[PDB]
Image (cartoon, rainbow, N blue to C red):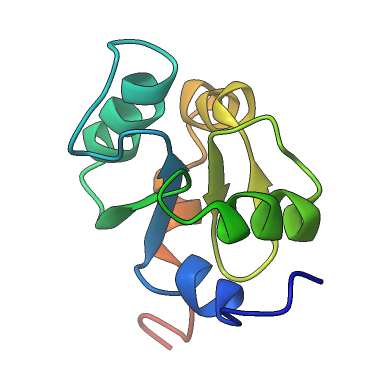
Length: 109
């Protein structure tokens, strides 16, 4: 545990849909990094990005927490969802929108 800066869960629980990557929405190569994004966006839901470089501690602090240094990483509800390969998977399948949104409580009754 890298003593210093204790607030990961919060980060992953900052925005409905969290997306950690190098460059953040700000910068994006084009694929892989931007991919997930485009998808996280294509969904139409709400999400955000974060810096994993600027905050090295977080970098490993996350991978060490999620146990998936194979960024990017998507966090939903509370448990780690997965990486692009994963995210895309859901989306592709067509079961991400309902995963991102966050179903809860009755609708009609």
